[PDB]
Image (cartoon, coloured by chain):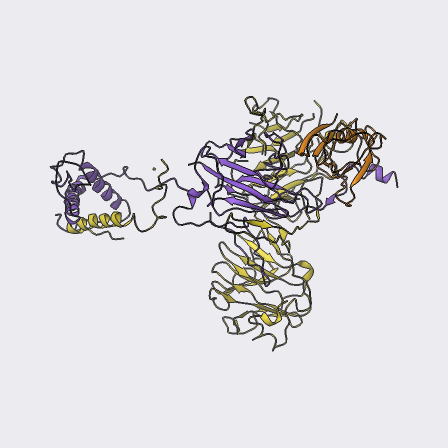
Chain colours: A purple, B orange, C yellow
Amino acid sequence: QHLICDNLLPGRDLLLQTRLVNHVSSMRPNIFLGKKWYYELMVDHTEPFVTAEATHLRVGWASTEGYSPYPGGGEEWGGNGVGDDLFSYGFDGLHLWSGCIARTVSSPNQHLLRTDDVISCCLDLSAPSISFRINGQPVQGMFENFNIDGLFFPVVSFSAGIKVRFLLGEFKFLPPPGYAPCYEAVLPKEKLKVEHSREYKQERTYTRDLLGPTVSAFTPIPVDTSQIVLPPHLERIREKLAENIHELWVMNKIELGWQYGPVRDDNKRQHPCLVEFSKLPEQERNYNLQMSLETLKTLLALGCHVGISDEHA
Amino acid sequence: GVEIETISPGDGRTFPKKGQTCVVHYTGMLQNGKKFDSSRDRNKPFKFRIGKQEVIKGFEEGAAQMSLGQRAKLTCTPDVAYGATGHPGVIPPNATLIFDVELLNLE
Amino acid sequence: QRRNPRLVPYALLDDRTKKSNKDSLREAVRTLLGYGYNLEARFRIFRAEKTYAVKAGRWYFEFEAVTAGDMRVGWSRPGCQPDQELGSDERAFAFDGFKAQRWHQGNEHYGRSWQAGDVVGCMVDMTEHTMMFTLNGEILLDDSGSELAFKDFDVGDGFIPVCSLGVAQVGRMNFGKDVSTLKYFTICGLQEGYEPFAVNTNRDITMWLSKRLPQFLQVPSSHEHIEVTRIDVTQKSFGSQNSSTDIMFYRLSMPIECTYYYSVRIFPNVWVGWITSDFHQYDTAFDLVTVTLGDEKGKVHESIKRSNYMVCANNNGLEIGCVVGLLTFTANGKDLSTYYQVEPSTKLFPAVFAQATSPNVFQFEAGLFKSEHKNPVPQCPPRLHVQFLSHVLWSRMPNQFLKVDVSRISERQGWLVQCLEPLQFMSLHIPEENRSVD
């Protein structure tokens, strides 16, 4: 038996291996992100061993396309910074993980995550470098040059008796490096929710409801304008309708209570382009000329073949 | 031999002395990412009298440095460990240790 | 437009910067009318646990369908693979309330449609081989107008409840437990003399669902038709004798920790790599991260690594993955440069990615390889030994529900995400083909 348990235990490859692992949970604040970007966190309580295991605090960023963040149904053991769709940071002795990598580049404290810590985190727009500040101190930059594909968000993971403060808007303490806050995607209509990070469950007495997956940006991509050919028999009516558009633009300021004057103003109601379509030169009326031209190019391009059926006026 | 990270500091100045028994909580694991021992596991704080030369060498070298509350990482050289023999059943021949020692008290 | 709040697309904003624009466009279209012109013109199969495969009884569960879409809900034998769709086998027996048809080996119209927020249901009589479907108290009839939906199904390996949601939907099931709070079993059911699942049990019935994340797996003999061979110099040759030819990834079985090389023969365009075991990306793409050092400030401190997986590309492509602690790349006697010589202590699956153009697509294997990889490690002549596999990245396999997750509270002032009560796994991991199961 000594011979068995010398030649067969310690290699740990032939038969299996098992141990208990603490339930990881990651949570994201409902802000997808395609300026630069930035956030904070402060830690309230850690209770670093309410398990017989080191409890983790991974703070950082993640991509989106792909990315099923499943508890126990992802990578090894459940984690953060374990797949390459993830980029996080934070330890007792604060070193990162990015793809289950343990590299221990230092800090000017060699600090824990204690219950009194400020984690400043920044992501750079299109210069793909991530850097993390502890208490304003730069923490010896590591992250560079990633796959900018899919959106981005903060992820932060935790598994203990742990509660922490989001500073996302009640901002508390935030340095400016780079700059733009996380508060710049709540602008148009959206809200500030924080969710479980992607939920094949939703826990309930009766039945957890289910979830078909998803359907998955501020670069403006319209229909192209200038590459549309105008025949001249359309161009006659186009110039006459640009004249009609300019005289309606005169009538618009007549309705809105304006006056012709040599001063190009809007604070004394004096406007220098209330004269006709051609009596304005082609550096103030050409912006309406080409507007009507491209409008009829689009009308000949949007599949509405408007034929000439009446008189042009 | 022993190469120490400070995981959590203590005070830095109340480091132990000969004739003392240190009360630790070591959770030592292999080089390869696999756990072999944990005094967090059976919830008994391990004790040992420095100067009587009980424990393996690198563990005693690292317990000389830590302070009254310092948690550290005693990455031991494989000749400072069990060695070319290894521990027959747990540690393989010529293996490296990555401890995790949270020193607590003195006696 | 600096940091001006006009960083918006047009359709996403309010109805304030649209009034003057749409009105001036209507004025231009009225100049056109004044000129006389008018402008005239995927899956999450949620299923119950295989040990609950009921096989002689009278069972029912009532399924709330919530939002419209692909909702294929009914019973199945446990051999329903999540990868292929529902119904198009002899193993799925379910009803699709949307579009009013029921699924077995193709289409057959049945029943009705469902209001968004109704509770559907599916009975089974095991003894008398009839499997009834309900909706909202009304027994769903055939096109013939008869109650018994499916008939004379064989009682084989039991039946398990299955819900197959679609794209952006929500479903809700009912698994006994809740006798007073059964919705439509109290109307039809109780009076007829049926029982739900969990009148007796004292658990929650743990479910399985497919993952989006693909994981590799052996090549079973009942594949489409892909025949890896075992030939012994020391070849594992191939073939893809099908019409279905999307992309077939290939992993050799066991990794290398951190001297000997390894030859891949190409018959027909073809990628060769060294997968680190976290490669779960199944597309027609070419993608995966550079961590830099710090000298307490940086300032030299750059080159660590990149890895994730590994890239290469007349008569035969005889490409060779030469190893070590680093990597290089040689091919067909020459040395295809730009090698990714970076591994601190990684594990590397020797791997190959390809599309099927023909049958007979590959072969496998200044010393050689096996004895740096097995247990006996002089052993300088190479040989294959029967642990070796030729894995295929399959898209989906079922995965456990994890009946309790964490007690969690998110909040408002400070946004206090808060978890206090700990929960632990019981998680093994197989070491030879590195991945973690619980």
Q: Nearer the viewer, residue B91 or A31?
A: A31
Q: Nearer the viewer, residue C45 or C2?
A: C2
- Image coordinates of residue A56 in percent, x first then y, are 63, 42
- Image coordinates of residue C304 in percent, x first then y, are 59, 27
Position of C128 relative to A42 (above/below): below
Q: Nearer the viewer, residue C239 or C113?
A: C113
Q: Could one spot residue C251 in this view of the protein?
A: yes
- For the image, the number of numbered tags is 0
**Residue visible at 47% across and 45% down in the picture:** A170
- Image coordinates of residue A3 in percent, x first then y, are 87, 38
**Residue visible at 88% across and 39% down in the picture:** A2
Q: Quadrant of residue C339?
A: top right
Residue at the far bottom: name it. Answer: C191
**Residue visible at 53% across and 35% down in the picture:** C287
Q: Is residue C422 left or right of residue C29?
A: right
Position of A27 relative to C183 (above/below): above
Q: Could one spot residue C267 in this view of the protein?
A: no
Q: Nearer the viewer, residue C139 or C18?
A: C18
Q: Quadrant of the N terminus of chain C?
A: top left
Q: Is residue A168 left or right of residue B85?
A: left
**Residue visible at 62% across and 56% down in the picture:** C80
